Image (cartoon, rainbow over all chains, first blue to last red; front, side):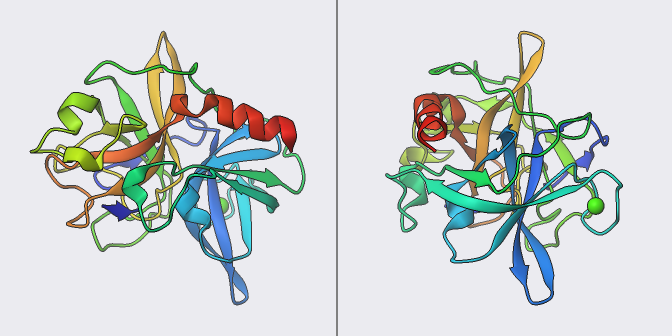
Length: 4
Length: 240
Ligand SMILES: [Ca+2]
């Protein structure tokens, strides 16, 4: 999961 | 937004730019949705850092005077109490910002319409993400606001093994996953606008993408599901  | 097009100036008047102070300047970090004249809805992870933040409404091009911008400081930050920075996949990626002044509404500055509580969109529902995030994985922010058409991917499909598996929760909305179009860093906190009964409403708050890249097939962009938080939102605004 990548916070964007 | 990867694989977006430039939005018209007055298409998405609830979109805001959340910026932090950096030296003698301000840097865009996230989007948000204006939901009251003095409240903005954004992602909790956008406000994890101990920074000075400001909101810009009526923004179109981050690098040029548009003649429509209003700039306002953030007076109070209320993150969802269950948010945990170490676990974006648990959800609760939502926060409300109380603005230091109420902004003035016009064709460039309007409140975002929120769905009624509990609303779930059918699979493949028409939505647009908007924002100034990177235009490529590991790229650079857009100058002008971008939009991309990202139909939803329902919970069953999105949480299936090929997609996000158990990383996605029913408190989230997935949209896109086509490998061409997607949110990307800098779009976080902004809206997913979905057309329902003839009117666009803000169904999502952009939360995350794959660590592998922004536009990855079967890794749709993931958003906090706004309609899961209506009571929470109303509660905060009423007590603040
Ligand atoms: Ca501008």
